[PDB]
Image: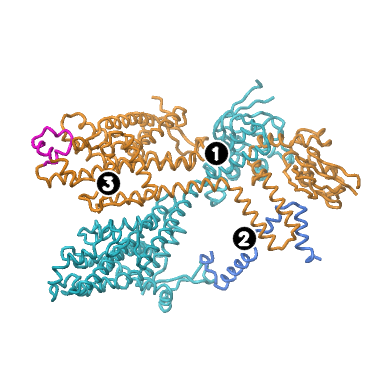
Chain colours: A blue, B orange, C cyan
Amino acid sequence: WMHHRMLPQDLRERVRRYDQYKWLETRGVDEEYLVQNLPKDLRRDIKRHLCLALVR
Amino acid sequence: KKIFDPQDKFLLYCNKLFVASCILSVFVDPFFFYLPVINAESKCLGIDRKLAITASTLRTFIDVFYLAHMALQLRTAYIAPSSRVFGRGELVIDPAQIAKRYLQRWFIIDFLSVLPLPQIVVWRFLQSSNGSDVLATKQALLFIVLVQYIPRFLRVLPLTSELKRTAGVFAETAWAGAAYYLLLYMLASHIVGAFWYLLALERNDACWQEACIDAGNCSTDFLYCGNQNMDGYAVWNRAKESVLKSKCRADLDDNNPPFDFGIYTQALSSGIVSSQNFIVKYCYCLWWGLQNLSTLGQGLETSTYPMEIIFSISLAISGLILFALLIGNMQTYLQSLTIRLEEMRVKRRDSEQWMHHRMLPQDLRERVRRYDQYKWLETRGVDEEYLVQNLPKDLRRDIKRHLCLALVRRVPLFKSMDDKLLDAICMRLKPCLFTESTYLVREGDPVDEMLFIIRGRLESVTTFFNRSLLKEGEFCGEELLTWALDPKSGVNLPSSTRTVKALTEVEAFALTSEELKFVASQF
Amino acid sequence: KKIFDPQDKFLLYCNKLFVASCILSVFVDPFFFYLPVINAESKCLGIDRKLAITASTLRTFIDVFYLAHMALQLRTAYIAPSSRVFGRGELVIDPAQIAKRYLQRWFIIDFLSVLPLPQIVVWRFLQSSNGSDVLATKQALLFIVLVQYIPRFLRVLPLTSELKRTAGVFAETAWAGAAYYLLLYMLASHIVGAFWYLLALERNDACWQEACIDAGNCSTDFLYCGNQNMDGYAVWNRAKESVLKSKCRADLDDNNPPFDFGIYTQALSSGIVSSQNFIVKYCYCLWWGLQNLSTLGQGLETSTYPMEIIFSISLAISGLILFALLIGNMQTYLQSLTIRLEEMRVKRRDSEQWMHHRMLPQDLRERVRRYDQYKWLETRGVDEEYLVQNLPKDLRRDIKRHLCLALVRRVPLFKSMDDKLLDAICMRLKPCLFTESTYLVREGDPVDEMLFIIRGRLESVTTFFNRSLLKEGEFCGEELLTWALDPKSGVNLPSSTRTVKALTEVEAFALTSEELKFVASQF
């Protein structure tokens, strides 16, 4: 797509960099799809473990 | 004239015992290749006569049975594009141009297959008392069957390669994907072993025809059966089994034989070319076919004769194709068989990756693994609501009334209600699952689904605090109901009054809040 | 100077008969490996001369035809990124820097392929009357062709391995995925059999060069053709066919021969190295190539000579690669071929699993199986509305007006209506399917779709009760229409008046309620 659209190479490096970083962090795993397929009590406990100290 | 309509049931059995005739016709053409024999008593090259009448009879008794198909597609309608039709096409039983509809593309391929070309080669040989025609019968059978393979395999291609893509009578197991590409091996082995037999006799004919000229006192007419009462045959008779033995013997231990038979020395040293038992000859050639198609020619030691080399190259290429087809149709079957299990394993590896990345506590990691294993044990990967939503509305309503009517008709406000609106309530009941010691609700939380218990036992305490049990058939969530039918609430999800713990693994049917407002707004 | 634009049609045939030249160029380089022969009359090692001029001519007549490609990308434009363009790139026909655009990366790989390196090895040998140069021609052809394989196979890699990933002129069948990886076998067999021939002559040269020194009365110049009128050749001539026979004979039965030829003893014992017929030699070497690439070297009995062992290791590895590529591209083709059938079988196994888990009655299980088989027979897995919604709006409107205009223009309130708004009505008609004895509606139920019948017959009773028939072209659901165009209703789905049973398998086009309010609110 970047060859078809002829993006500048500074914009092509920013796309490649984000895709490599997202692959390094998530490894392809859709985290919100995993969380939304959990029971509501398990969702709430996992989300309170991950995100309560940040909000508080 | 009664020109037929294309979806008649008579043109469903006359295309059922018809494709069987197209299948059994490509098994009969290799039997013309076992016609030349060697008479080891007389050391002459002959023709098997009661295999000649057998293969001619069994190919003619299929082709004039086939001749009642272009005499019936002669009476055939078709479907043409139009917007007048209301029903996706016109039927044309007018006989003036359906003749061209048949005889413009799919007549020449079907006409060049009922031609009795390998039956007239047999004809003027078996109606004589002269041995001179063993040459012509063996001459005119390799290339005629080899070129009539193309129309006879092209009239089975649309009925196999597109009846495997969208099959008609098979769904459930492996009896048409493995047992088709394994009988495609047995057909190709049947064709290849018959070529091996016939070409083995042609190389022995070449040896004998060249070792008879070197002797000088021999004409090549003497090498054929039925030429014994010719002049000069008596001086050749007393020198047959020294000339043909010092020059045309076939052994598998000779590395410098007087004639190189190559891949055909196994046929002449075993003696199946002079075999009186046809079961021995057919089985020995069919196994050579299967062994050299299965192993891509690996063990072929050809001579430096280019037709034999080209026949070996064809075996290697055909075996590569046949093997790639078999393992590709077996992997396609097995991959579609364990699709939900592999999806569960991908989803299970994803959850371990995500829980390791987020560094969840191990008590929260066990609760995730437990629910995923329980959901795999109950549903086996099957999305039940997607299956139900793809059904007709009458079938949906009957299935949902079978699954969920007794559950809704135990609620006292729903049992005395209706039938119209409770059959709209039990179309939104979706299945929930709860592992053991899962808190379904705790006090202070908003009640957001009513649960009608299918399986497993539950528990209920409120404010050692007058505990209440729940088991198979009872429900839980009546605080949501009276809230939702009352209009003096607004969108205000009411607080819980009980702490409800799953004592076992629980199945239920869930009716959420926004699916309960829709059935409460029907008043 | 007329510097060309990259999508000219002249640079579409000069890249059509160009990649054919790049394909036919890697088939000509193995023919230089059949240049050394053995003259079995004189027992000297020679060079085939009218295969030398043939391979030199047919490689030069491709490379100066290739020399009109870097003389044409000389006149070439390219596309560069910019936001000024409005059209995804600038074309640069300025000749000052497009020269560096060509000659910075993809010039050196393309220049090290038109070099006449195997044509100048042939040159100073065939322009002499001296036999001394048979050594140098055989010396300078293995490694030069072996190292020029890399630029000549790298200038076919972007035009094959990415013209198989996104093909240009092929969609529909198996004539570029099986018939490409089977002619990749025939190319590799052509290269490997020529290496086998050439290395077989080098081992025979090694045997003769070491068995001539042990005789003592022989110089190694005597083993080459054209050195017969040298001094001391007459004393070597009367001892050739005892020295070279007791020391350098090749038989396939010797387990302790005087010289081990290994995998090359089949080449010298068959006598193709001294063959006068080039068809015999080429076919025999090509079949060795295919037989040992197909079976990954299995039947190779090498000597303890390390270059021969390394050549065998290369055959095993190359055959493993070639086989994995062929079966992987055949499984990828076959899996994409039966994708809808395997989806139907997965969906069919899911429904059996779900109906067994829920324990449906068998009358409800037969109705599910019947609808799934009918839907597979009609649609073959194809989502028609997803196909239609991915079309351009003009093509959508024309296809939908072909399918559904005569159906809508038989409704009396729709035929006299419009063209503007009925062409918006027949964009929401979606296909419904009904198996036999399916109740499309029953009385008291809310009518929620109007149905315009395509195929199959129906039935209609209301309150033995003045029955009404329905067949191909009629519609059903006029209670929904008058309800929806009347504004004195609100959102109030009206009750049914008829019981409508599918007498046959029915196709229809459905217009639901909320898709009928949108076309009723256009007044």
- The label shown at residue B172 is 1
Q: CA distance from mark 2 to mark 3?
A: 60 Å
Q: Nearer the viewer, residue C161 or C48?
A: C48
Q: CA distance from mark 1 to mark 3?
A: 46 Å
Task: Kindly state the secondary structure of the residue where label 1 is placed.
Answer: loop
Q: Chain of mark 2?
A: A
Q: Is residue B232 magenta?
A: yes
Label 2: which residue? Answer: A28
Q: Nearer the viewer, residue B117 or B457?
A: B457
Q: Tell me the amino acid under the disc marked 3.
A: Thr
Identify whether C206 is placed above or below C343: below
Residue B265: which disc?
A: 3
Q: Are marks 2 and 3 on the same chain?
A: no
The image shows residue A53 at horizontal and vertical percentages of 79, 66
Q: Indicate which label's residue lies in the foreground, 2 or 3.
A: 3
**Can marks 1 and 2 be said to lie on one chain?**
no
Q: Number of numbered discs present?
A: 3
The percent coordinates of residue B256 (x first, y second) are 23, 53
- Residue drawn at 47 percent across, 31 percent down: B7
Q: Decide if residue C488 is in sight here.
A: no
Instruction: Let me know if marks 1 and 3 both belong to one chain.
Output: yes
Q: Is residue C394 left or right of residue B359?
A: left
**Residue farthest along the top direction in this orientation:** C464
Q: Secondary structure at mark 2?
A: loop
